[PDB]
Length: 400
Ligand SMILES: [Ca+2]
Ligand SMILES: [Ca+2]
Ligand SMILES: [Ca+2]
Ligand SMILES: [Ca+2]
Ligand SMILES: [Ca+2]
Ligand SMILES: [Ca+2]
Ligand SMILES: [Ca+2]
Image (cartoon, rainbow, N blue to C red):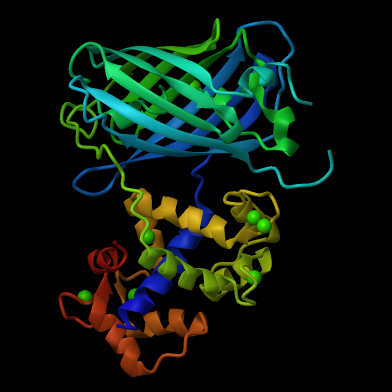
């Protein structure tokens, strides 16, 4: 009914602003002192029975050789991962499909390294990992190929030691960013290929929030025609029954993106896109945000758009909005993020969305609703019947 429908549209607009306010990409910066790069990013692992495990990544890369390399301007990589099982495989294994693209530098105002030439076709890949987490040792072998033209990787991994003592998803980032698609205007910022064929050292520390950490060191280089990733991993301070050693993480996160859900995203999109030209500008994003209480600067609005602007044109195209909302529904929000969403409606911070607060939000968004059909909205969400929406009830409206 067009009352549940109003929860979706308004709810979707609030999680869109949540997405636009978060940092989900792989942020690369030059590190002149090491002749390399450094990176930071946040990974989300869905917890099988509900919630999310965050993994905070810090990364450094260093050329193995003394050839000249490209030190980039600030940019990011966007990564889409799909995990699956080979139904003919009896060993503990993971099948990985990964697409990696560089963006985050807008179009305007101007080279292409020799390493880049090694990546114009399909390149075979080998991966070898030796790990030790809280004294539990394991090895992993992987094979596949990479197609940098489309930023595409296909890789199958076997645990050669028997049972993997951590969940496979926690190893994805560790187990070849030289396969990233860099667009034509950003070819001078591709450190990864510029270091080849002699290769780079890749190091990370990965902090699992409320749990232990991984430390990784990898050598990434050509052995003949093959791109080889050789890794050592050490994990300490894990909890025996946390999400990692207790294996409480989801293996396959669904890309179920229905025609019904796309249509719901288009309804939220059209709240931002008030002139109906199919794109959202800083002006339009600024207008919806001020209407909900917030007061961002031109610069903040430019950054928020930059975070999802795949084509660098300075606006959120409808397809870029569909891409960001698919990510937002594929991976679970932290409690801190759902509470932020709740506080948009819960104006006074008392733990309860009153019908006055919900209308304030609605009529502030230019949504004409009679006291009757505002009450229908509260009805829809209000399980415990107090005529208010508490946190646990909000968390129910905001689910698939
Ligand atoms: Ca580090
Ligand atoms: Ca527009
Ligand atoms: Ca764009
Ligand atoms: Ca465009
Ligand atoms: Ca939310
Ligand atoms: Ca309130
Ligand atoms: Ca209630």
